[PDB]
Length: 207
Length: 207
Ligand SMILES: *[C@@H]1O[C@H](CO[C@H]2O[C@@H](C)[C@@H](O)[C@@H](O)[C@@H]2O)[C@@H](O[C@@H]2O[C@H](CO)[C@@H](O[C@H]3O[C@H](CO[C@H]4O[C@H](CO)[C@@H](O)[C@H](O)[C@@H]4O[C@@H]4O[C@H](CO)[C@@H](O)[C@H](O)[C@H]4NC(C)=O)[C@@H](O)[C@H](O[C@H]4O[C@H](CO)[C@@H](O)[C@H](O)[C@@H]4O[C@@H]4O[C@H](CO)[C@@H](O)[C@H](O)[C@H]4NC(C)=O)[C@@H]3O)[C@H](O)[C@H]2NC(C)=O)[C@H](O)[C@H]1NC(C)=O
Ligand SMILES: *[C@@H]1O[C@H](CO[C@H]2O[C@@H](C)[C@@H](O)[C@@H](O)[C@@H]2O)[C@@H](O[C@@H]2O[C@H](CO)[C@@H](O[C@H]3O[C@H](CO[C@H]4O[C@H](CO)[C@@H](O)[C@H](O)[C@@H]4O[C@@H]4O[C@H](CO)[C@@H](O)[C@H](O)[C@H]4NC(C)=O)[C@@H](O)[C@H](O[C@H]4O[C@H](CO)[C@@H](O)[C@H](O)[C@@H]4O[C@@H]4O[C@H](CO)[C@@H](O)[C@H](O)[C@H]4NC(C)=O)[C@@H]3O)[C@H](O)[C@H]2NC(C)=O)[C@H](O)[C@H]1NC(C)=O
Image (cartoon, rainbow over all chains, first blue to last red; front, side, top):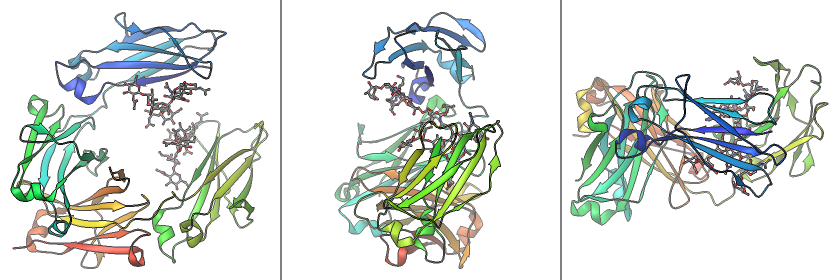
């Protein structure tokens, strides 16, 4: 019998007016015997009609996969609207329902702090530039690094972690050739979040 | 449904502790709840597992569990632990295997980072412990001061770095005053690839 997965928009998508945030309702394990899928969409319990439902794609395990995509208003998502996908199939005793929304709670502003490498790490060929991002809510967030207006690609960011006050934190780690750090180049940690002014801040780091 | 859980990292690294592998069984009904367990170590049956007396969950389903005690070195030497389960609702007995992640162990580099200047505005401050370059990801991190344990800390999960090794960050939050006074704070790290399975690095206010 069929299964349903509801996917939220990307954090970046909801924070920038230029981007297009979407909610996606994927349905898997639809059979040949009853292959028709109907989708119904609701926003805060109210039906909407603007969703674009893709034609169904057969898969290698001889089950059908069908996707539906609802485009979402930036402010609706940020204002906490609930997005419901109702999925109907003649193989299902009742239509499956999933709901998704922005995590509930008062948004909190990220504190962004850049940390230089430890003295001890200077023995090595490469060094670690650390960006601590703390006290934010909800956990939806995007983090990036750049230098001299151009993007630094050798970095990893930890997932968000629930702190003891109910807020979230994370760390991002940029790895650069020691030489570059020594020369005095400026490195910048960019952070995108709803509780930031213009949904964006950045903090710089150098010696 | 059956889920096989490994030991806690701390348990396998200290001879005093008792590492255990746990075989948790979910969705057990009242009509046919007569669960059995068979355990094998490297394909060889072992009879020293203790099965837990049962508890029941919020739904009509029961939550059931068995626990096998494990030799420290067996787990560190990569032995395979198999849990076999039979039930009246089951067409066939479910079975699962688990073991330590394969690969050459790699030693953690541990670096302590003091708070950013900007965070000094606040009532509390963040002491950061960067732990990098370790393999496998099983690891334990702790903080202490004056030989006594600091409780107000959180540690990120391990994150896969670009070289195939893992890193993480641990964040200790202390009252700003304490940092100012010049107290010494220490980040303790436990891992298989460390000498005596243990290292620690200290942090304090350096004029
Ligand atoms: C038959 O085949 C199909 C398709 O398989 C084809 O494709 C290949 C994979 C390959 O196998 C090929 O041979 C086949 O032709 C199978 O469909 C698959 O079915 C599984 C379920 O069995 C389904 O479930 C998992 O997927 C969720 C994540 O999916 C995203 O990421 C995947 C990679 O990680 C992608 O493959 C997938 O497309 C999808 O990708 C995202 O798509 C959106 C929309 O397009 C994009 O916007 C997005 O960017 C993109 N991301 C990425 C990274 O690409 C995963 O989340 C599901 O997890 C939940 O379900 C489990 C319960 O089953 C829970 O254990 C789990 O915790 C998750 O749910 C939690 O709990 C509940 C929900 O249960 C929530 O309330 C809660 O919030 C949630 N989170 C928690 C608790 O934290 C799940 O693991 C696969 O996605 C699906 N594959 C595809 C391609 O659709 C089918 O199984 C086969 N059938 C049989 C019988 O064999
Ligand atoms: C009736 O209720 C029960 C009880 O649940 C209670 O929990 C509450 C939160 C509440 O919501 C309510 O549900 C109840 O009060 C329901 O059962 C629960 O749900 C599922 C059963 O479908 C089951 O499996 C999921 O969790 C697995 C891990 O659970 C650990 O962590 C949970 C917290 O996140 C704990 O709740 C849980 O106890 C367990 O905790 C660990 O336990 C050991 C004990 O030894 C400790 O040592 C350990 O420290 C401890 N804590 C933690 C934090 O670790 C999870 O692994 C499962 O995920 C995999 O399998 C899914 C298949 O369902 C895949 O979809 C998914 O991708 C996962 O990943 C892949 O799995 C394949 C194998 O399938 C691997 O090969 C592959 O490598 C792997 N890839 C990955 C990860 O990339 C799964 O999500 C819960 O355990 C169970 N809860 C309990 C408490 O037992 C039940 O649904 C209800 N009944 C009905 C009919 O609905």
